[PDB]
Image (cartoon, helix red, strand yellow):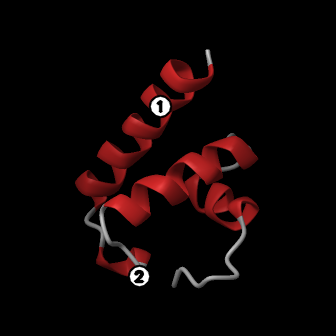
Amino acid sequence: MKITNDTTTYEVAELMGSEADELDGRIMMGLLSRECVVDTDDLSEDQWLALIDESQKVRREQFE
């Protein structure tokens, strides 16, 4: 997927899997911004999985 200025957190969440919710999507949007990722095609599977893990760490640290 290409991230635009109008991509929604619901769309990013859908990229993560059916279990992810809008907060997962907003956290992941922050991570993709920090990593300068526009095209999700560019992420290797291992890179993507590391970002998923990190979004779960951020969800529990910065919100619980």
Where residue 43 appears, as percent x and y from the top left, is 30, 69
Label located before the other in sequence (1 or 2): 2
Secondary structure under the numbered disc 2 in the rendered image: loop
Q: Kindly identify the residue that appears in the image at 49 percent across and 55 percent down.
A: 30
Is residue 8 or residue 20 the one in the foreground? 8
Secondary structure under the numbered disc 1 in the rendered image: helix
Where residue 20 appears, as percent x and y from the top left, is 67, 43
Which residue type carries mark 1? Val
> Compared with residue 48, is residue 54 higher up or lower down, i.e. above or below?
above
Measure how far apart labels 1 and 2 are at the Cα level: 22 Å
The residue carrying pointer 2 sits among few (fewer than 14), some (14 to 19) or many (20 or more) residues within 10 Å by Cα, namely few
Q: In which quarter of the image is residue 9?
A: bottom right
Give the labeled residue for mark 1. Answer: 58
Where residue 41 appears, as percent x and y from the top left, is 38, 79
Side (left or right) of 19 relative to 61: right
Side (left or right) of 35 relative to 28: left
Q: Residue 17 carries which label?
A: none
> Compared with residue 51, is residue 56 higher up or lower down, i.e. above or below?
above
Q: Kindly identify the residue that appears in the image at 62 percent across and 82 percent down.
A: 5
> Compared with residue 51, is residue 36 higher up or lower down, i.e. above or below?
below
Give the labeled residue for mark 2. Answer: 39
Q: Kindly identify the residue that appears in the image at 62 percent across and 63 percent down.
A: 12
